[PDB]
Length: 159
Length: 74
Length: 116
Image (cartoon, rainbow over all chains, first blue to last red):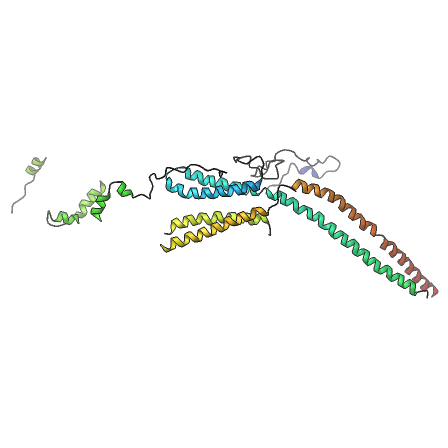
């Protein structure tokens, strides 16, 4: 609601005395609730706030096939660990563990999208070339019709 | 091979709610008995400020006394 | 949206929401009803599990990744530029023919008006 005054009052005056715009920053930005740290990797980072159990290979497909059995077996182990020990504390760590697993699948699956995004870019470059050639050939064809026409006219004129 | 984050399940049958808790807690014969005492009380006496006694219980000089108060026979 | 990622994510969410309520529901409502529900629920969960397995094979492998795609785009960028030149070479021939015929028709109209 409140406009800034002491950084704007010096605008109505000529010459090179008006202030320049600020150069581009290369530091962390504090605007908003979000941390929004500068030069963040495009892929989501689970390095901070999440424990890492991932392999050196970093292949999503191998992990996805293994992760699926583990969540399912845990689901089945969580089903009967209630009867084996109702008053035990470990049930809520299993839910949390389950929550951690849920955090992981989505985190791992999101790995594919950046690669997927890159693929979308290539067709745009590719399709225009497929379109530009057609326009040029069509134009050439149209021109040809006209030229053969004026040759017919030049054949019929002097006779 | 092993799935991620397998662990050891608890002891095979510890104390659960799937056991018969009463027979384990030695209370069977009382139930097998059980499954008015005013009447029980009534048999000893006649029948069974009963409004006043309850209120008194809700919140929760024998020789000299006799000498002090005299009640006319007729 | 016809996207592989959207379909895979959706299946996982249904399983999470579908199974959390179902176990609670089993605890919630207790002969004939309990047995049928067990099969009905097992059926769906089983179906979802099968679907997840089917989905993983479809996605692309480690080879031909994003860096490779960018590399492919490079060679492509040069090709596009050349294609553009083709049309700029094609043009201006119609323009010169058009200016010639406008000059000719202007001369004819001038001769027609001067012969009077």
